[PDB]
Image (cartoon, rainbow, N blue to C red):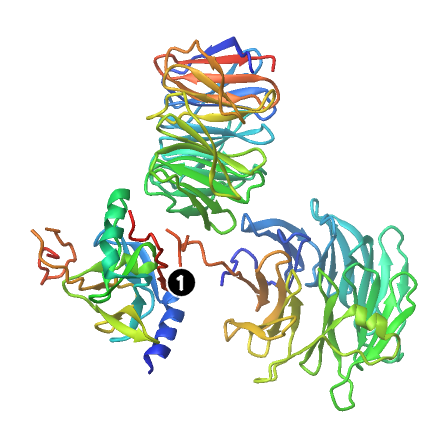
Amino acid sequence: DGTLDCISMALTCTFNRWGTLLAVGCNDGRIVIWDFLTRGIAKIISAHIHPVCSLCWSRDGHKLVSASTDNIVSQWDVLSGDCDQRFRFPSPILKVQYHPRDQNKVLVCPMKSAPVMLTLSDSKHVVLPVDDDSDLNVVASFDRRGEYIYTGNAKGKILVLKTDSQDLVASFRVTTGTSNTTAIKSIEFARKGSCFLINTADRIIRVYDGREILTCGRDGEPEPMQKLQDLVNRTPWKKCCFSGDGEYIVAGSARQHALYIWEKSIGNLVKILHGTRGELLLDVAWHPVRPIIASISSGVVSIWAQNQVENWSAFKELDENVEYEERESEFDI
Amino acid sequence: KPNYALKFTLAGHTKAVSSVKFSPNGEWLASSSADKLIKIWGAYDGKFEKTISGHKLGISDVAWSSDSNLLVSASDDKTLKIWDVSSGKCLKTLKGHSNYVFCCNFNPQSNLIVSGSFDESVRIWDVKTGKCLKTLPAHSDPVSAVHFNRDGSLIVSSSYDGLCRIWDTASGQCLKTLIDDDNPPVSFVKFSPNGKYILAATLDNTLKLWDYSKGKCLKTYTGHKNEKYCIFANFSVTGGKWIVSGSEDNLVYIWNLQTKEIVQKLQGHTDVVISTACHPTENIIASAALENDKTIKLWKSDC
Amino acid sequence: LPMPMRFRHLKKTSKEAVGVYRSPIHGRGLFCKRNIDAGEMVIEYAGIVIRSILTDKREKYYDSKGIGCYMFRIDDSEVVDATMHGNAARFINHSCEPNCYSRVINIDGQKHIVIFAMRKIYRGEELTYDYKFPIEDKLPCNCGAKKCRKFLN
């Protein structure tokens, strides 16, 4: 539905705060900041020699946190492209995430170690707690306002901490239905409201409302707002994301390189988008204020927009025949 | 009511002037003409700054950049040309219009250009690469005037076929089509400063202010004479709220904005007052007339 | 397949099956965007369903407004007038050799004038049918057909 030839080795992308720019990582380890309106590249940053697998914009948009595969995280000013700060860790980093309401702070999910929240002003770090002490794979994310931290382990356990004190404000383990746990693949939140989603190893996305987890307390049984899956193919989900408003949810079937689109309230599947059967789906993102969806597959990015009835359909356009309502004086002088 | 008096008379274009525009900082006055020449002049003293040539045919429109650093020139050579106002360098020459380009305007963020041509198609252009990003079979007649809204989300277009069409910028979607029960050749169109209204001139001695959210004409302005040429209209805001325009009777008409009543008639031009420009900051109005006058006159009032 | 089911399918696929472009026949016209099989529903000439007695009062009305009449006779009693309210079917040119043909169908009691395909129509083809306009005293035709009557009438 529209691709870009000007970028190669697309690996990970991230919309800015207003959905005007897109920073995509490349295998060479370069940042390609490409613009939507001019439909061209806005910037090229020599980030790492190692490909970049995690990228996040700052709220003001002037900072981008990038993670190399060399366990090298670095902050870059979008105007200049300089490495503002640079750090390295053990257990290679799985993800970075700016704090949405404090760009000085940034959480980092490493591979084998617990996620740690650092600051840029001071090169300090706060190691977030781990429930089972043996997960070795815990994804973590700020909420919409950056007030709480949601951490999900490979054993389905879900901890909600407060971002400042790291104190356990809520907890619950998700189930595979019967009695078993499932590897929490990812935690996503809505940029609007409080609904969030969890991708798990059961190939079943679970949509909740964080207020219900907060009122559920520690070690409770919160039910999901929704349960979403491909009941037909039972396909895993490499990457999923909400819509900009938060009423549409998309999942990327890397198994068959497709895109499933459900709703939030009803949860019925909006639609499906099919990509090149030969392409391996890698990354998925939604335009924050547009029905536009960016996909990264086999190093190539594709764009999926959604237009209205007009752009040619605007006499007064009607859809179905209209019986004329004759009047009393319809034949009168 | 205004009391605009002639302060400076400007001239030098060897041919018929087609457009005069005040720089957004109010520092310069750009005057385009069919002589393939543009003339930058001092906006407060009538001091001729320089002449910028390079266009191959007559120039039908010119538009300033928001930072008062660039000028787009739409010429009859089917080309646009983006110039640095400080150096006069042809930074870009926009090719792709299949016929005479008549109007041109920058986006509110000055990074994009809209262009109307005789080809009856509106082209949407990059600035930093000068690349045509969109092209729309907008009208069934040569385009007269194109303009941006307050932010750059909407593009209004007028043409000789009498249609005033509002189009989406991000998609080229023909949002609205304003009709006034007839087919009056619309020679000029532009958004309101608040982006809420639209001023369109029709070639029947009539100006019309429409509501965008309502899609209906709110006010009408007559008394002038305009039936053949692209006579520009501007909003006088630095003093009282007025509507200033040229007329085929060598007059410079100024109506009240709300009451639609003529508040001044600036006479002194000998030919049709072909182009008008209102100062962005001061109560200064540049009125340029056609070849039988070849003069541009600065008018300053006290309100 | 049921005429109602076929009609629902036609109204679902009409927006993406056909388009309107610059036409070498005349001005703008209907072109095929996806290969259309013979006899299948191409497009409804949708519009305002009126009675016949009200045609003239409308026509003269348009004659007073200088707006062209877009009317097709459903039958001796009804007419689809698309002058003010219609669909893309108002841009179907005519050819003496049509790959399409108009037929009136009855869905749930209401009559619909549907242009179906006289033959297997392929993508890009301009859609044309037989208007069957009665012989007047003359509109030249530029349909390009070798059998062209040189005149619709």
The residue to which callout 1 is attached is A319
The image shows residue A91 at horizontal and vertical percentages of 81, 71
- Please, is residue C102 above or below residue B223 in the view? below
Relative depth, front residue between C73 and A218: C73
Whether residue B299 sits left or right of residue B12 in the image: it is right
The image shows residue C19 at horizontal and vertical percentages of 34, 60
Residue lying at 83% horizontally and 68% vertically, measured from the top left: A115
Q: Quadrant of residue B222?
A: top left
Residue lying at 87% horizontally and 74% vertically, measured from the top left: A217
The image shows residue C145 at horizontal and vertical percentages of 13, 61
Residue lying at 38% horizontally and 74% vertically, measured from the top left: C8
**Secondary structure under badge 1?**
loop
Relative depth, front residue between A24 and C14: C14
| Position of the N terminus of chain B by quadrant | top right
| Position of the C terminus of chain B by quadrant | top right
- Please, is residue B14 above or below residue B125 in the view? above
Whether residue C40 sits left or right of residue A111 in the image: it is left
Tell me if I can see residue C47 in this picture.
yes
In the displayed orientation, state which residue is furthest to the bottom: A178
Relative depth, front residue between B68 and A48: B68
The image shows residue B62 at horizontal and vertical percentages of 46, 28
Q: Quadrant of residue A141?
A: bottom right
Q: Quadrant of residue B42?
A: top right
Tell me if I can see residue A91 in this picture.
no
- Please, is residue B299 above or below residue A326 in the view? above
Q: Chain of mark 1?
A: A
**Crowd class of label 1 (few under 14; some 14 to 19; many from 20; radius 10 Å):** few
